[PDB]
Image (spheres, rainbow, N blue to C red):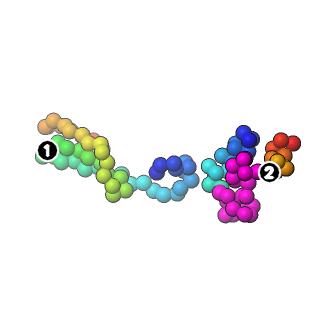
Amino acid sequence: EYTHEKWAFDKIQNNWSYGENIDEELKTHPMLRPYKTFSEKDKEIYRW
Amino acid sequence: SPGQQGRISHTDLVIGCLVDLATGLMTFTANGKESNTFFQVEPNTKLFP
């Protein structure tokens, strides 16, 4: 959760926001949401 | 601006200063808005911007 929050913080302060797609131009990423909203399999991106 | 993310916003800032030489009152404005700070001075005073 910490690792996610740190990755999310850096992005949100660089003006990135939540959205369905991963767009470099529009500054959007679907993972810019609380770690609690991730499924157990999705949480493996950080736990593994 | 509150919660501003650093110099990400590319906007200029304008600050204005007003002085009254007959009453000794100095005030400031920012972007056309008033400010709560003010100063009072005694007669026969010299000031430099």
Cβ–Cβ below 8 Å for labels 2 and 1? no
Q: Nearer the viewer, residue A44 or B17?
A: A44
Q: Nearer the viewer, residue A11 or B20?
A: A11
Tell me what residue is drawn at x 53 percent, y 56 percent.
B9
Q: Is residue A41 visible?
A: yes
Horizontally, residue A8 falls left or right of residue B29, namely right
Horizontally, residue A13 falls left or right of residue B3, namely right
Tell me what residue is drawn at x 48 percent, y 58 percent.
B11
The x, y position of residue A31, in whole percent, is 73, 54
Residue that sits furthest to the right in the current view:
A48
What residue did someone put label 1 on? B23
Horizontally, residue B2 falls left or right of residue A38, namely left
Boundaries of the magenta span: A17-39
What residue did someone put label 2 on? A39
Residue count near mark 2 (Cα–Cα under 10 Å), binned few <14, some 14–19, many ≥20: few
The rendered magenta stretch, by its main secondary structure, is classed as loop
The x, y position of residue A27, in whole percent, is 67, 59
Q: Nearer the viewer, mark 2 or mark 1?
A: 2
Tell me what residue is drawn at x 64 percent, y 51 percent.
A12
Asked if the magenta segment contains residue B8, the reply would be no
| A44, above or below B42, in the image | below
The x, y position of residue A35, in whole percent, is 72, 47
Secondary structure under the numbered disc 1 in the rendered image = loop
Residue count near mark 1 (Cα–Cα under 10 Å), binned few <14, some 14–19, many ≥20: few
The x, y position of residue B19, in whole percent, is 22, 48
Q: Quadrant of the N terminus of chain A?
A: top right
Tell me what residue is drawn at x 37 percent, y 56 percent.
B31
Secondary structure under the numbered disc 2 in the rendered image = loop
Tag 1: residue type?
Answer: Thr
Tag 2: residue type?
Answer: Ser
Q: Nearer the viewer, residue A35 or A27?
A: A35
